[PDB]
Image (tube, rainbow, N blue to C red):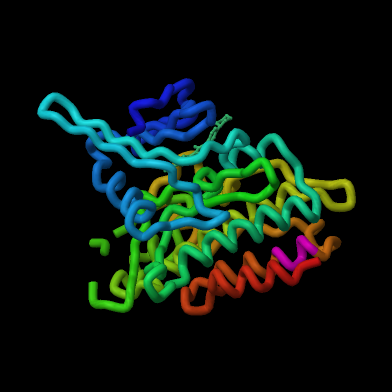
């Protein structure tokens, strides 16, 4: 079991629980400890790795899952590979980017998101999966320059068979207009895919600001840094996105670079108020693959 693991250092804490860096047979591993209030998030994220056999170069790599439960207490561990460089959010604050490194990040995310979204058939197939909490803090930077998508505790699934949610359980800063509007068609699975594309558009913006061009770059800032306070409320986001119909502003420098200009058009096509008008994960991958 994973009782042979040494918990060295805590790297993340929050409502979900905690994530620890740990050692196991000489190798660093990440250990997510779920509080007993997140037990269903533990099982869901485990079942995707345990039963659906979720694996992809840009999805966080599962290692093991353990639950031990007495009447005294219950422990819930999810064990995955460890990524020293941390989250895309931490990375972007300490690093600038160039044409190649930026593309590798962006295309890497689009590849992981599209594999999540696309249903696969057969004995080794997978249902369509919606993340529902895409954001820079849930994307990890790998040593090789690529990224992988991490937290799947809120993901939903859809297969070719009648069948996974009630409402709005994501990070409010990244919620799409139809979520803040409550216009979202909760009964159409594509609705949740289009929510991810909105979040992915914000992450594209975050990354692009950090790509240097013509000797200039932008400090890191979160989406909507200029119009909402830290930890914005549901009403604050609805006012900026729906009523004021605000969108992250595009610096004028982006248009003097080919890469940044292509990204700008991609972002905007992820931000249409109408979800049906937004690009798909696959077409975002294709477009990104053709750049440079
Ligand atoms: C086990 O499962 C998850 C694991 C991770 C995850 C995997 N490898 C690395 C990290 C990580 C390590 C260090 C940091 N830095 C904090 C700021 N200072 C610099 C170091 C950031 C991230 C993590 C969090 C992520 C999500 C899950 C999950 N299942 O949601």
Residue 159: give x, y in percent of width and height: 33, 73
Q: Is residue 173 above or below residue 84?
A: below
Residue 75: give x, y in percent of width and height: 26, 31
The answer to whether residue 242 shows anywhere in this view is no
Residue 271: which quarter of the image? bottom right
Residue 252: which quarter of the image? bottom right
Q: Main secondary structure of the magenta part?
A: helix
Residue 141: give x, y in percent of width and height: 62, 44
Q: Give the quarter of the figure containing the C terminus.
A: bottom right
Q: Residue at x 48, y 54 (%)?
A: 134
Residue 6 as seen in the image, left or right of residue 223: left
Q: Is residue 7 above or below residue 82?
A: above
Q: Residue at x 40, y 75 (%)?
A: 121
Residues drawn in magenta: 259-263
Q: Is residue 162 above or below residue 144?
A: below
Q: Work out whether residue 282 or residue 22 is closer to the camera in this orientation and state it.
A: 22
Q: Work out whether residue 169 or residue 7 is closer to the camera in this orientation and state it.
A: 7
Q: How many marks?
A: 0
Residue 150 as seen in the image, left or right of residue 105: left
Residue 199 as seen in the image, left or right of residue 166: right
Q: Give the quarter of the figure containing the N terminus.
A: top left
Q: Work out whether residue 238 or residue 24 is closer to the camera in this orientation and state it.
A: 24
Q: Is residue 181 magenta?
A: no
Q: Residue at x 14, y 29 (%)?
A: 70
Residue 142: which quarter of the image? top right
Q: Is residue 287 above or below residue 249?
A: below
Q: Residue at x 40, y 46 (%)?
A: 233
């Amino acid at each position: 079991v994973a009782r042979d693991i040494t918990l060295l250092e805590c790297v993340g804490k929050g409502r979900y629980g905690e994530v620890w860096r740990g050692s196991w047979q000489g190798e660093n591993v990440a250990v997510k400890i779920f509080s007993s209030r997140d037990e269903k998030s533990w099982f869901r994220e485990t079942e995707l790795y345990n039963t659906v056999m979720l694996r992809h170069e840009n999805i966080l790599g599962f290692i093991a899952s353990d639950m031990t439960s007495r009447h005294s207490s219950t422990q819930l561990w999810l064990i995955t590979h460890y990524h020293e460089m941390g989250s895309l959010y931490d990375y972007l604050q300490l690093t600038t980017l160039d044409t190649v490194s930026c593309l590798r990040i962006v295309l890497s995310i689009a590849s992981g998101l599209a594999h999540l979204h696309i249903e696969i058939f057969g004995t080794q197939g997978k249902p369509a999966i919606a993340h529902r909490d895409l954001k820079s803090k849930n994307i990890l930077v790998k040593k090789n320059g690529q990224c992988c998508i991490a937290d799947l505790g809120l993901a939903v699934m859809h297969s070719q068979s009648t069948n996974l949610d009630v409402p709005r359980v994501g990070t409010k800063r990244y919620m799409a207009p139809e979520v803040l509007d409550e216009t979202i068609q909760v009964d159409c699975f594509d609705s949740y895919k289009r929510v991810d594309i909105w979040a992915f558009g914000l992450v594209l913006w975050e990354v692009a600001r950090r790509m240097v061009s013509n000797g200039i770059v932008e400090d890191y800032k979160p989406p909507f840094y200029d119009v909402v306070p830290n930890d914005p409320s549901f009403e604050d986001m609805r006012k900026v996105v729906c009523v004021d119909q605000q969108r992250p502003n595009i610096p004028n420098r982006w248009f003097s670079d080919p890469t940044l200009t292509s990204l700008a058009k991609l972002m905007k096509e992820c931000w249409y108020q109408n979800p049906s008008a937004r690009l798909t994960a696959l077409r975002i991958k294709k477009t990104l693959t053709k750049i440079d």
